[PDB]
Amino acid sequence: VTVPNDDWTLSSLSETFDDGTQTLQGELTLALDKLAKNPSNPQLLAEYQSKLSEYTLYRNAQSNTVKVIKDVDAAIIQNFR
Amino acid sequence: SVTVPNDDWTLSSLSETFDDGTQTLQGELTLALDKLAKNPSNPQLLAEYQSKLSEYTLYRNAQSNTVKVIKDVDAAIIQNFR
Amino acid sequence: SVTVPNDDWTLSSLSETFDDGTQTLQGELTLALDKLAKNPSNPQLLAEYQSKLSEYTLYRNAQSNTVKVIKDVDAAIIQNFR
Amino acid sequence: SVTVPNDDWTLSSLSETFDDGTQTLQGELTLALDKLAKNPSNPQLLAEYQSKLSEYTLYRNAQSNTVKVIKDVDAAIIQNFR
Amino acid sequence: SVTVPNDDWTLSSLSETFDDGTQTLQGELTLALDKLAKNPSNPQLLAEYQSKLSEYTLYRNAQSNTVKVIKDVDAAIIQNFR
Amino acid sequence: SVTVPNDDWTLSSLSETFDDGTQTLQGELTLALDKLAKNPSNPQLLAEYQSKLSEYTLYRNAQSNTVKVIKDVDAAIIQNFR
Amino acid sequence: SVTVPNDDWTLSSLSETFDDGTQTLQGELTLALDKLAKNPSNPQLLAEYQSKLSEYTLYRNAQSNTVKVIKDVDAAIIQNFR
Amino acid sequence: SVTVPNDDWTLSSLSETFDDGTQTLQGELTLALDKLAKNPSNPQLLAEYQSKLSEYTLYRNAQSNTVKVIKDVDAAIIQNFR
Amino acid sequence: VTVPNDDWTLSSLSETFDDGTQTLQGELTLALDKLAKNPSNPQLLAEYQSKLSEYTLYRNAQSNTVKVIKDVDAAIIQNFR
Amino acid sequence: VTVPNDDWTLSSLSETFDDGTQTLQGELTLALDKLAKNPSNPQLLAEYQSKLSEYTLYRNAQSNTVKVIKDVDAAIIQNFR
Amino acid sequence: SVTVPNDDWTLSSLSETFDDGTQTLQGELTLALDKLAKNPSNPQLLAEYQSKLSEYTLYRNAQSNTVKVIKDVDAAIIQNFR
Amino acid sequence: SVTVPNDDWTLSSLSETFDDGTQTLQGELTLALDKLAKNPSNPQLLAEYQSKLSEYTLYRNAQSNTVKVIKDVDAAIIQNFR
Amino acid sequence: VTVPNDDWTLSSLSETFDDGTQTLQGELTLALDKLAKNPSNPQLLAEYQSKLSEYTLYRNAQSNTVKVIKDVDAAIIQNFR
Amino acid sequence: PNDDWTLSSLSETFDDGTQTLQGELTLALDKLAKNPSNPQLLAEYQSKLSEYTLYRNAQSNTVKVIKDVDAAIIQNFR
């Protein structure tokens, strides 16, 4: 839960992204274990592909958002002088 | 479960739409495979099994390629955040 | 909402213009996807779906790149306020 | 079932079209087979059995080749999605 | 409809051009398929069906490849906006 | 111990399904082969041996082709990970 | 009507130079595409169409890359004003 | 050796997970390969060896693709330290 | 017809292939007409077979050469940036 | 012998296939010499046919296995980048 | 050694801490490289070498980026001495 | 016209060095192409053409990559003038 | 023999890859000459296939490793300024 | 076995290594054109033709593999 208000941190944004994507992590873990059991089921492969792609997208979005907010903060800081 | 270009639909939703869009094929393939296991010499059984297997292969390839393309588009859009 | 190099047009306005300017294509894509999920074996259906998917990918890439370019120009103009 | 080049027809449609269009031949072949297994000595019965069996074999080969060609075309069109 | 290198033509329009440019072949192919289903023994019918099937396969492959090449060119051009 | 289009089944499961689905044929073939090796002169024995051999050959070819097709599909799906 | 390293030429001039320099090839490509849509079975037609398509793709890529490089040079020069 | 999206797991852990998750298949492959090398004429042996080899190939390809994807994600995250 | 010099194109290369193999096309057409008139003469069949084989080889060679040159040209283009 | 472990190459696989069916080469050579000496014994012909078929199957199996393993190894390499 | 934001710790000390944290990986990489040079065809060897190389690359990139960030912060603090 | 790591050598000089160093190859390729166009059925001619074409492709790719690398290094050195 | 320590270069890495694979080069050259002598022995063909495959894998791995190390070095370089 | 050998050199090596067999094939072709009825001549011609086909296929495949490896090495320059 992040709102553009007084109290929220970058770590708060990272935890917000992590908690928003919670079912996908567990489903990816289950699919990974199932694939390790037998890597020949087409349905298993398709589900694992979808889960891995969504996980990659989530990681990239989180990292880019944190980088952009850090750049904004750095830009604002230098105006002190 | 239907996918529409609107606010909410994910890759998992797309895969579920592909799976549930053609569900009769999986059951027909199962039945044909069981019949072929019973007697693998009936020409009609062989023809039906061939048709079902080919359609299943096409469905799987289409699903995988669609998922790949949508993932590529999503990855391309994200990189502009910086 | 038309976008003109004038006083009133924002980044969200540009994105909405890109979305509205190509709306029937999204409906065609939805219909093609539903019909393909119904039966993924019709050659004409497959070709139409390929065309729609290609158009959608190009549209998304163009929209994202245009938004990025406009944002870069705005950021470049900002740093000269001092 | 008759297949036309339109938006809705599958490989199963082609198989069922080949099955339904050539339908009296299977019945005639079965009848000739029964009447020949009863007494395999009549030259006319032998000639009719030969004709029906040849037509049945030709029909099966044609159906298999058509299904294979259509499946190959559909698979080729799929690859260009990505 | 034709798609000359003017400002008004799209990938879906190119696919429509490829389709409507060769529409007699679809009807001839389905007529030959119906006739073959009726009787799979006439050599002339078999030759006509073979020719129609080969031409249809070539047309579909050419259309798909052309659409893919045009999509590749469009994607390559777009990514230079950034 | 059968194969269903669901979450859990592997290629070895498909091979086991193909092998165990038609198990009487192997025993009948072994017995007919032993009898033929004992004395190859009775027409009924020869006909039974021919039928069993043909059915076994068809079963083996069908199993191999199905396994190869499933392998191709699985290989196709894998490549889209990256 | 050409582009030279002098005091009057812009990016639109470069694009017009690239387009006007390759004008007969576009017409030949259009004619080949129309002929192919009329009948996609002439090997000479296929070879000529392949050559024209390859030349068109190379021309588009070269034009886009040249415009991008010149824009990069101009942007790099600009940022040294202050 | 369990891979979970938690604090403690690395790429080598992923490789070990993929390896140890598929252990009996390696032993079955060894036994089948030895039996085939001793006498490569048993159809059952050939089918089993084919299945085991296909499963091993799929496992290796999936492991490599997963490792590459995770490496790409980690490299993307690292660059943002800048 | 085609020299590694300033000006020669893919269409020019295809025209070179067409011009180099011109007698064979006419011989094949004449043999095809003769076969259509009467497909019984063994010499006619042998000559038609030879001409058809040469035509197929020529077409394959032309297509492969065009493909390879297109690949080379596309590879060179990417380095403009 | 070859095990999916640290030490085994493609040459190891080829030598494994050769050595496993090692008596077959000697049996085939002896049968070939006996056949060339007098090609009229039905039992000799049957034995030679069996040995030749087994040799052909062994060669095909070895070639296909080596090809598949090489393909897997090459596919793994491309992910180094 | 230990690296805490306390009274005494240096950038070179930070680099040495980063090196010492990753010490087993260097030896494993040496062993894998030597074994691959011995025989560059073992799939297990290739997978292990890929994992070790990826982890080494990530470690080097992270170390360099952290050192650069710390140097930038220190330079920023220095400039305000006056 | 030899490229030496000293005061005087440019990108054009490097490209001309690549061209001049391998000039008999182009003549051999031209002669082979002429012979093939005369009659495209001689196996020795086909082998020689394959060898020459492969060598030419490798030469062109190496030249382009070397030019790009040197240009990148030169651009990197220039940027530090300010 | 290369160690991630103070003294080792890219040229040293390539030389290590070359020297480590010395038996394979000799066996490949011998097999190539023997095949040029006569391309009929099945054993010769199998050995040549194995050697060629191993050589291809070794070259690909060497090139990819050199590229990766160069990429790491280039990435570290830019942090100087 | 050194730093100086090209694809053309490889093709020349393959051609020159199998040179007597091509001459034997040409002689057998002339003899067969004389009279296509000698069983020994037919068997020899069959053997020579099979050997020539195998040699051509092996040469082409080797050249293709070496070219692929060289092309793969080039792309890693940048």
Image (cartoon, coloured by chain):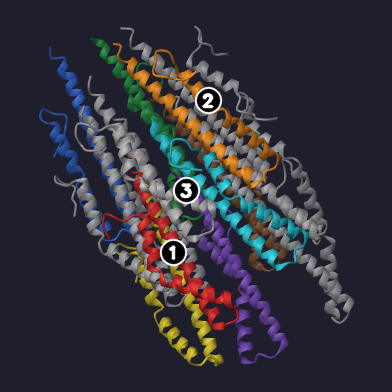
Chain colours: A green, B brown, F purple, G orange, I cyan, J yellow, K blue, N red
* Residue type, label 2: Asp
- Mark nearer the viewer, 3 or 2: 2
Residue at which label 1 appears:
N58
Mark 2 chain: G
Position of residue F18 relative to residue F81, above or below, is below
* Residue type, label 3: Gln
Q: Position of residue J61 (x, y in %)?
A: 46, 69
Q: Position of residue N38 (x, y in %)?
A: 57, 82
Q: Secondary structure at mark 2?
A: helix
Are there few (<14), some (14-19), or many (20+) residues within 10 Å of tag 1? some
Q: What numbered label is drawn on residue F79? A: 3
Position of residue N45 relative to residue K69, above or below, is below
Task: Same chain for labels 3 and 2? Say yes or no.
Answer: no
Q: What numbered label is drawn on residue G19? A: 2
Q: Secondary structure at mark 3?
A: helix
* Residue type, label 1: Ala
Q: Secondary structure at mark 1?
A: helix
Nearest the viewer among N9 and J60 is N9
